[PDB]
Image (cartoon, coloured by chain):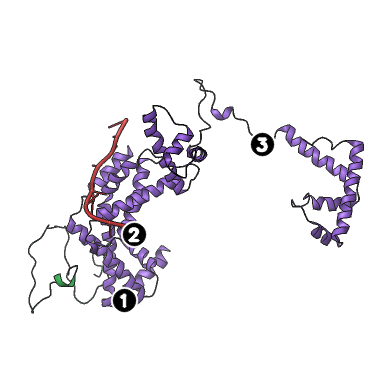
Amino acid sequence: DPVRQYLHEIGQVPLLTLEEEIDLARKVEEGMEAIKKLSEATGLDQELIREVVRAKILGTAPDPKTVEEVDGKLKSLPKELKRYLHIAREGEAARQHLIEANLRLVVSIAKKYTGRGLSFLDLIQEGNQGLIRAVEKFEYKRRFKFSTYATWWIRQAINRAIADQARTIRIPVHMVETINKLSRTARQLQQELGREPSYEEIAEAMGPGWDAKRVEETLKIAQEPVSLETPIGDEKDSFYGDFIPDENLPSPVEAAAQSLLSEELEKALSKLSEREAMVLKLRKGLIDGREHTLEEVGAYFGVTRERIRQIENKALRKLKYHESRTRKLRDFLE
Amino acid sequence: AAIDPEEEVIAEAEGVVHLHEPASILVVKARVYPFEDDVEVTTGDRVAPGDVL
DNA sequence: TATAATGGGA
């Protein structure tokens, strides 16, 4: 039971008082402003100082070079500018404790979104992502409790997660909201009718802009795929996919037919001059896969569009003549 | 310091400040090193006996 | 983007 493990772990961290909540949110904003004034004093990027401070706080172990040489430059600064180093360090410590003390709130919000395709712990962890983004741009000066800003961010990160991960075949966000609107209406009219609706009446219930054909096609994408390992019958020796034919792999008869066709066309083209045959192979895409127009073929052979057309037409009625006598190519014709 | 400059305690004259009404007292098993001048050790790294503070 | 919301559920 990993849920009891995590709830016990977030249980060890006690909740924080309104005084502590103001103090931690204060040190966070002070640390973030201390970083920006270090980007003016030293001249390097915000995120660089951000990670070098995060490193030296949450863990010991380029590690020996780039990380320590940036920290070394920061350590070799005047006293008036090294204040902002210490302020940034404890400010990043405040961000850690601000997150840890409110992991208890993420669980209280995430539990309502269960049964939508993501497990509980997946509902807690994407919610924890909202808790981090909530802390990072939380400003305590507005005099609002941290729970109000977080709750909006926990729900944003969970809803966004369900929209992106729950479906096996990825679906846009608005369509997920649309599918939820459709799925809620069919359950209350099931209770009202005692039976499932037709597509016309659920479309009449959905409002304007919804007809019987749109509800059928949006519900069509709403359904999740079937498992190929769905068991068939009580016997434990067959899955669904054991009875599905391969519609894409060619059969032995199909594979031979395409080879006999390529062989019989080569033998047919061999009754022509090599230019006559090369023109036809360029015009039909047998060389590189694209039908070359009369201009490219004339450029290849150094002749005009009309000269190529005559070569092409003469080569065809020679093929038709030989085909009327051999009848090799008369089939393959579907 | 306070949220708005009006509620900020400004010292009206030269004096000595004391602290008295604490929400909570945190006793940490540690030992204390007062410093003058400046410091080179920064907040959060571990140290060995004899290392310069 | 801000009332506040802080340990699951079979």
Q: In the image, what residue type sits under mark 2?
A: Thr
Q: Nearer the viewer, mark 2 or mark 1?
A: 1
Secondary structure, mark 3, is loop
Residue toward you, A238 or A55: A238
As helix, strand or loop, the secondary structure at mark 1 comes to loop
Q: Colour of chain A?
A: purple
| Tint of chain C | red
Q: Earlier in the sequence, mark 2 or mark 1?
A: 2
Q: Nearer the viewer, mark 1 or mark 3?
A: 3
Which chain is home to disc 2?
Answer: A
Asked if B51 appears above or below A223 in the picture, the reply is below
Residue at position x 91%, y 45% from top? A318
Q: Colour of chain B?
A: green
Q: Residues within 10 Å of mark 1 (few under 14, many from 20)?
A: some
Q: Earlier in the sequence, mark 2 or mark 3?
A: 2
Residue denoted by label 2: A60
Pointer 3 local density, CA inside 10 Å: few below 14, some 14–19, many at least 20 = few
Q: Which quadrant of the view contains residue A320?
A: top right
What's the chain of the residue with tag 1? A
Q: Is residue A326 above or below residue B47?
A: above
Are tags 2 and 3 found on a single chain? yes
The residue labelled by disc 1 is A77
Identify the mark at residue A249; answer none if there is no mark.
3
Which is nearer the eye, A294 or A213?
A: A213
Q: Considering depth in this image, is C9 or A236 the residue closer to the camera?
A: C9
